[PDB]
Image (cartoon, rainbow over all chains, first blue to last red; front, side):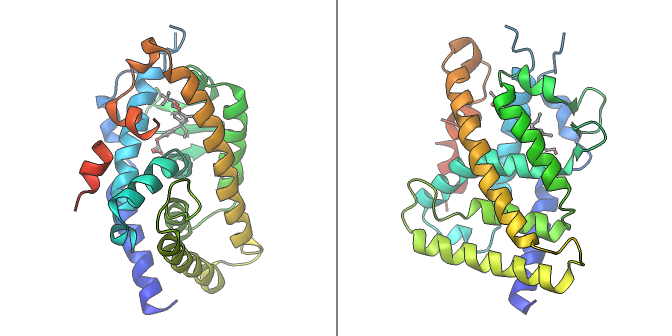
Length: 238
Length: 9
Ligand SMILES: CCC(CC)(c1ccc(OC[C@H](O)C(C)(C)C)c(C)c1)c1ccc(O[C@@H](CO)CCO)c(C)c1
């Protein structure tokens, strides 16, 4: 790892620590989970997602190179990646003990039923769980995890990106930092084809993004559902 | 709107 690559990693780790609270303190402020419209978990999960978008923005701002992109390109990258980075960053609370996201409260332990009660079907939910499990099984170090989120966000192939050459240059610098980290630090057998496996997770995220988008488009078209969404969610997923 | 305003600078 070069001095620059070490600095990239330190910046990303700090950014994550500043935008991911592992105590889940802020969750009391969300509208309450209702588990008893049948979309009873829509308000709570809308608030959780809206909060998560704010954190992804805060993280992206710190990725080296990101703020040198035009405003338009920064916006395109964030609107297109937000759901994906949310899925990635949620892996940190995900637990293979019961295939749930454990966020420090009995009622903030989210399961497949919860996501269905925000309007989603198993067409999204089952691949989502498979994704979380596969990702957990990679046993990523925190450095690998934050690099992967950064690479996800800085993707030159997102629809509407203007300066794809600059976005690619930034992404390749992050990708090379990741490959060097794996070579230098990740022990066998976990390191074997790790970079490839991580790149595959990015491809899996594109598929989950497409399905989430389709389902979101449908559920949000119902004014009773849309009225329960936050302005930020409406804008970012719109 | 909200995104642009947050990213402004
Ligand atoms: C990504 C997994 C999940 C699981 C509950 C989720 C939430 C809402 C969803 O859909 C929402 C609907 O699409 C709408 C918008 C209609 C309400 C979908 C598909 C999935 C989730 C999201 C953020 C989050 O916080 C994490 C990640 O930020 C921090 C703690 O780990 C945790 C712990 C879980």
